[PDB]
Length: 206
Image 1: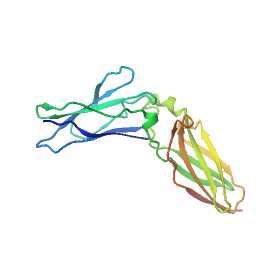
Image 2 (image 1 turned 90 degrees about the vertical axis):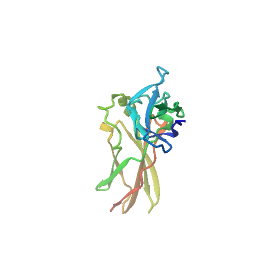
Image 3 (image 1 turned 180 degrees about the vertical axis):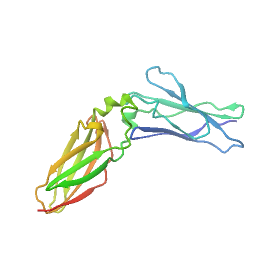
Image 4 (image 1 turned 90 degrees about the horizontal axis):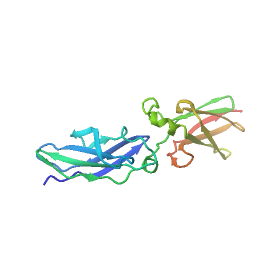
């Protein structure tokens, strides 16, 4: 009949969460309805921005305001005067399923001191998502300092960064060589751990 959507997938990265699905080719153009089941009510409700849409995706970022509790989502298809039944996604928990991509990392020096600026431009503004303040209060970055030509490797952590923008100064032993640095985001120490940035390297003279 009017089959249900297929291949449901919730993809969450850097707090942008999007639901995707696929649909068979029909004579005309199907539209879809997406619902969300929040943990508190334990009942499905309509995702307003995703009713009667032709797209096979739905941005859920505004429906998710809990990082530890579960959400379910579901989609039905509308084809002419006919509807499919809903198909439900896997359980979704932001803390478990949400990915944190590599941070943006800038590397400079003042004399023999290396300066690391690290942040995630993708993270949403706290002013636009006030529920995020609590989460950002737990944001930290771990930074790995490597000297190949030497060849050593220490670890640093920076937190309580204003506007989620962290800066770190680091003393370089010596000091005619090259140092390479990478970083990862952390939320709640190790409950959420992001991918490493690629290495940035810099020369520090004597």
